[PDB]
């Protein structure tokens, strides 16, 4: 009842008091990660059938 | 044909069928013949810690039947200090100091009643009701019991099940035949009636009351009553499977042999009296006691026959004037007077009198006007021909007292008052019950003794509950004929089938180690004609019904959530299960026995309902819009 | 009164978090990525149909070798396939028919599963006599088991309809840690690449980020209008996506503590059942209640392609560690492998 509503506001304090970066920086990190690994993504563009385990290989 | 038992898998269905009825108890099973037999097998050959109790129990059952007291004094000695005694006391189960006190107490005074060891029987059972019975349920003997109970509960007899021999009777509704049941070979009498005649003579109320009265008295194996074992009916005739009595009736033998003496009459009176005592303990008044209903076997012993006019009085306390004129008591004449068994004690007087003189005590001038006979019986008192003896006088004078308040058997102790008449003072009623006295007349084994139409329908409805089977008698027949041998080959057929699954298998067992609810065979026919009847082994789980053929685990199923309903349908005069599936499709099942149909119909409804109610409250499983 | 002051303070803290998040909403992922070229039309073909399950499939999970995968079905079985050949390496009948989830241990030594039995059962795949036998039944949840994932061979995280998650000590069979916070059935969970964190998605329309070693909820994410049925981390562990009954996927970034994008479409009205990323994170794949799997451009929110090869719900999917293929599980009994 009260120990629960008190348990809540204490939890929100842990979530409110944290460090947050800008969305612009967070979004660039993601875009940079994708770019740095586009060549390793076999679903991004098909790979030679010789390198495809589920095709002739 | 040849009794074939179901395969052990029938246990899965049968055990749930019985459990639902509370018939899976030590009392309900032990008290059965095939039950006791199989249970005894398990205890003597498989649970050593219980073998001694069954040994002792059976030695007491043997002692109970000893007729001569000199035997009972000799056996109660051997038993009391037997190795079974120093084997029960040695182990865990020494009889209570109180029980042992009673026994040797009667031994001291050298008194050996047949129930001498009864305090031991009760304690013996009190020590078989728990773990011992539970260990028996877990064993393959109860399994075999389920296989037998499935046969018993799946009985649908037809005339093809009996080999009929000569005719042994005849009347206004049908003949009585001598036949042999093909399954076991036991000799029975088949009393065939005819719905065509019954309707003509308006005797439907009688044909139904005879089978309800036969049901009430056909328990206990009374030796002095033509008792019923089965009841069925083709689409045209009612059938009773009764005790075989190929020896004519007294009404016939009376005319041929001539009048009987007090001694020859005494034999019949004693055997008859024991028949009445049997019915009267089951609150059944016969009301038609006459020589023509007294049958003889091939040895000359008698039985009361044709319970058509019998009646219950445990609640009814019956009605009015029913019987044969000349044998009906006063209370059985005043159509406004209630009477119980006292109607038979009076009817026995007229019964025996006609055997000693040759005519009813109230019909001398050979009068056919019932109002005359009913007048002499209700008014003037009977006066014996002086040729009757003093004791014979006391009996008939007592059994014919118009006042029920002053008649033998009507004074509060029943037949125990007739049995004590000095006329029977020379008789040992124990030996009477055992049929050890010489019959006065032995019939020769070659006797001859002694249309219209109308259609059917709605009268067939009045017989929808005619088919019947007395459990006690079908089991007894089986026990005394084919039981032990069937159980022998059935054991070999099951062992070789297991040995074969060994060479092919190492797979089993599909129904174990999961949440399987029930399994067994059924016949499936699918959507549509484009399939035909196919037999498969089904497994019912909480969320699906799987099935397989032989030599391959199940590749097909049917989920509880796609099952819309479960209806009972009709096909080829055979009842089936109709499963409506979501996509408008249908799935029909046909079980091998009536119990299976009841248990599958029940377990499928419970399974799919609980499952659909369950899936609905599961986000990941329920259907979303 | 003391409860009215705690409710008002709680809503004040919610304002701070809301305003604090807005404070760093300087730009949108859509804007940042307008310069990269679109991925184009993503087309894949069915390379394998995995046949064997007799009824609906509810879950699968790839092994770390990108070759073996386990799946649990309405038929009360776990099947462990070899996707290359399609052969079955194991067919595990379960002691409870209501299995809803299953997991594959990184070591490949064990799988797990559970459901309406409220139990997470561990199965040893490397036994003495080659026999597969139940080697542990983790009991403790008061509701069904919705998902589970091995940290290693001695630890497993589980989510339950009882509102909670838990970390387990597979040896002692005891709940090392409880994760209490959600207010609805927890439906899915995903482990960060470092296994030091994980995120859950429940029917309260929210996902939470949990500290594995401290049993504390560190951040809460909202925005969905319906239950979250699926969740998965971005390959680098700094973000994750969610699939909801509200017909949308959503991307959430941890450092920015808020939602970056939303993948939806006026023609897609059914709910999402499963989400997985391509190896590089460029593609967000999601199975739908309309029998389809849609491939989304993770960075630009376009729909690149559609995997259409099931006659009923796509209930689960997964992408292999080597990124070579996607597996789709369906209510039609079948698993298919695409690339
Ligand atoms: O002819 C019989 C008869 C013959 C045999 C047996 C018998 C019983 N057990 N063994 C032989 C009993 C019987 N009872 C009665 N009636 C008269 C009757 C005939 C047709 C319809 C109704 C009554």
Image: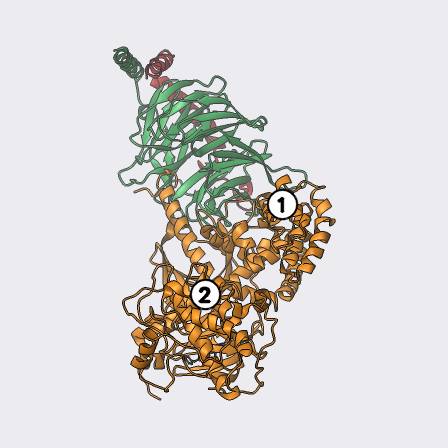
Chain colours: A red, B orange, C green
Q: Which mark sits nearer the N-terminus, 1 or 2?
A: 1
Q: Is label 2 within 8 A of ligand 1 (CB to nearest ligand atom)?
A: no
Q: Looking at this view, is B619 or B484 the one in front? A: B484
Left or right, B452 with respect to C277, comes to left
Residue B77 x, y percent position in the rendering: 72, 52
Q: Residues within 10 Å of mark 1 (few under 14, many from 20)?
A: some
What secondary structure is marked by label 2? helix
Instruction: Identify the residue at horizontal 52%, vertical 26% (top origin).
Output: C168
Q: Looking at this view, is B243 or B395 the one in front? A: B395
Label placed on residue B279: 2
Does the residue at mark 1 contact the one at mark 2 (Cβ under 8 Å)? no
Residue A8 x, y percent position in the rendering: 34, 16
What is the spatial separation of the Cα atoms under label 1 and label 2, in whole angstroms? Answer: 33 Å
Left or right, C137 with respect to C316, comes to right
Q: Residues within 10 Å of mark 2 (few under 14, many from 20)?
A: many
Can you identify the residue that label 1 sits on? B102
Question: Is residue B603 in sight in this rendering?
Answer: yes
Give the mark count. 2
Q: Is label 1 within 8 A of ligand 1 (CB to nearest ligand atom)?
A: no
Q: Looking at this view, is C301 or B524 the one in front? A: B524
Q: Quadrant of residue B301?
A: bottom right
What secondary structure is marked by label 1? helix
Instruction: Identify the residue at horizontal 35%, vertical 82% (top origin).
Output: B197
Of all chains, the one bearing label 1 is: B
Observer-side mark, 1 or 2, equals 1
Left or right, C125 with respect to B373, comes to right
Residue C261 x, y percent position in the rendering: 33, 27
């Amino acid at each position: 009842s009260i120990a629960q509503a008190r348990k809540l506001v204490e939890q929100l304090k842990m979530e409110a008091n944290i460090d947050r970066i800008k969305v612009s920086k967070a979004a660039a990190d993601l875009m940079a990660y994708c770019e740095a690994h586009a060549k390793e993504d076999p679903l991004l563009t098909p790979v030679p059938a010789s390198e495809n385990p589920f095709r002739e290989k | 044909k040849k009794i074939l038992l179901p395969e052990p898998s029938i246990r899965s269905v049968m055990q749930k069928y019985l459990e639902d009825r509370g018939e899976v108890t030590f009392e309900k099973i032990f008290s059965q013949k095939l039950g006791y037999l199989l249970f005894r097998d398990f205890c003597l050959n498989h649970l050593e810690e219980a073998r001694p109790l069954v040994e002792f129990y059976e030695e007491i059952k043997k002692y109970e039947k000893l007729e001569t007291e000199e035997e009972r004094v000799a056996r109660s000695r051997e038993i009391f200090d037997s190795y079974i005694m120093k084997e029960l006391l040695a182990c865990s189960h020494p009889f209570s100091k109180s029980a042992t006190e009673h026994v040797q107490g009667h031994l001291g005074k050298k008194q050996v009643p047949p129930d001498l060891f009864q305090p031991y029987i009760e304690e013996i059972c009190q020590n078989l009701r728990g773990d011992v019975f539970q260990k028996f349920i877990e064993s393959d003997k109860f399994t075999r019991f389920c296989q037998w109970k499935n046969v018993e509960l799946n009985i649908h007899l037809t005339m093809n099940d009996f080999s009929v021999h000569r005719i042994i009777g005849r009347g206004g509704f049908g003949e009585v035949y001598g036949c042999r049941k093909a399954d076991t070979g036991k000799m029975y009498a088949m009393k065939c009636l005819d719905k065509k005649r019954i309707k003509m003579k308006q005797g439907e109320t009688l044909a139904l009351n005879e089978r309800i009265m036969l049901s009430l008295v056909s328990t206990g194996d009374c030796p002095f009553i033509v008792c019923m074992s089965y009841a069925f009916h083709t689409p045209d005739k009612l059938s009773f499977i009764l005790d075989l009595m190929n020896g004519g009736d007294l009404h016939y033998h009376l005319s041929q042999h001539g009048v009987f003496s007090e001694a020859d009459m005494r034999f019949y009176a004693a055997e008859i009296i024991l028949g009445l005592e049997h019915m009267h303990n089951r609150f059944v008044v016969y009301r038609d006691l006459k020589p023509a209903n007294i049958l003889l076997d091939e040895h000359g012993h008698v039985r009361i026959s044709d319970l058509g006019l019998a009646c219950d009085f445990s609640k009814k306390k019956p009605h009015a004037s029913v019987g044969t004129h000349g044998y009906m008591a006063p209370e059985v004449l005043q159509k406004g007077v209630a009477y119980d068994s006292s109607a038979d004690w009076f009817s026995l007087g007229c019964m025996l009198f006609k055997l000693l003189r040759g005519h009813s005590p109230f019909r001398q001038h050979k009068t056919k006007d019932k109002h005359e006979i009913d007048r002499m019986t209700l008014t003037m008192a009977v006066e014996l021909p002086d040729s009757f003896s003093p004791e014979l006088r006391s009996l008939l004078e007592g059994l014919l007292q118009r006042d029920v308040n002053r008649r033998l058997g009507c004074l509060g102790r029943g037949a125990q008052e007739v049995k004590e008449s000095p006329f029977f003072r020379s008789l040992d009623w124990q030996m009477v019950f055992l049929q050890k006295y010489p019959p006065p007349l032995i019939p020769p084994r070659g006797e001859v003794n002694a249309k219209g139409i109308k259609l059917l329908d709605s009268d067939q409805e009045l017989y929808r509950n005619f088919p019947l089977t007395i459990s006690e008698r079908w089991q007894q027949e089986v026990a005394e004929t084919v039981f032990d041998t069937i159980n022998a080959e059935t054991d070999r057929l099951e062992a070789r089938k297991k040995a074969k699954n060994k060479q092919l298998g190492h797979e089993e067992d599909y129904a174990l180690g999961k949440d399987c609810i029930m399994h067994g065979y059924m016949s499936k026919m699918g959507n549509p004609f484009l399939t035909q009847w196919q037999r498969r082994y089904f497994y019912l789980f909480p969320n699906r019904l799987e099935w397989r053929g032989e030599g391959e685990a199940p590749q097909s199923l049917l989920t509880m959530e796609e099952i819309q309903s479960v209806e009972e349908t009709q096909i080829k005069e055979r009842k089936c299960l109709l499963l409506k599936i979501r996509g408008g499709k249908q799935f029909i099942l046909q079980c091998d026995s009536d119990p299976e149909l009841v248990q599958w119909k029940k377990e499928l409804r419970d399974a799919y309902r609980e499952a659909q109610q369950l899936v609905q409250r599961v986000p990941k499983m329920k259907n979303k819009p | 009164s003391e409860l009215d002051q705690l409710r008002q303070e709680a809503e004040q803290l919610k304002n701070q978090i809301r305003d604090a998040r807005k404070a760093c909403a300087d730009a949108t992922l859509s804007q940042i990525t307008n310069n990269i070229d679109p991925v184009g039309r993503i087309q894949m073909r069915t390379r394998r149909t995995l046949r064997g399950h007799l009824a609906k499939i509810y879950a699968m999970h790839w092994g770390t070798d990108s070759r073996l995968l386990v799946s649990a079905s309405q038929d009360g079985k776990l099947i462990i396939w070899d996707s290359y050949t399609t052969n079955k390496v194991h067919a595990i009948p379960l002691r409870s028919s209501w299995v809803m989830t299953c997991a594959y241990a990184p070591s490949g030594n064990y799988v797990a599963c559970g459901g309406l039995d409220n139990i997470c059962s561990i199965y040893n795949l490397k036994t003495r006599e080659g026999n597969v036998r139940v080697s542990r039944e983790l009991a403790g949840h008061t509701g069904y088991l919705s998902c589970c994932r091995f940290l290693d061979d001695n630890q497993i995280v589980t989510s339950s309809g009882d509102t909670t998650c838990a970390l387990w000590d597979i040896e002692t069979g005891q709940q090392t840690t409880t994760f209490t916070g959600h207010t609805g059935d927890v439906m899915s969970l995903s482990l960060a690449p470092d296994t030091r964190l994980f995120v859950s998605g429940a029917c309260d329309a929210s996902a939470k980020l949990w500290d594995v070693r401290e049993g504390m909820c560190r951040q809460t994410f909202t925005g969905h209008e319906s239950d979250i049925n699926a969740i998965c981390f971005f390959p680098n562990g700094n973000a994750f996506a969610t699939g909801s009954d509200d017909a949308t996927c959503r991307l959430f970034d941890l450092r920015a503590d808020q939602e970056l994008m939303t993948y939806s479409h006026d023609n897609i009205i059914c709910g999402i059942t499963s989400v997985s990323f391509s190896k590089s994170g460029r593609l967000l794949l999601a199975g739908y209640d309309d029998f389809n799997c849609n491939v989304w451009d993770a960075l630009k929110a376009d729909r690149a392609g559609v995997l259409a090869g099931h006659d009923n719900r796509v209930s689960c999917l997964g992408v292999t560690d080597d990124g070579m293929a996607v597996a789709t599980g369906s209510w039609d009994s079948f698993l298919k492998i695409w690339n």
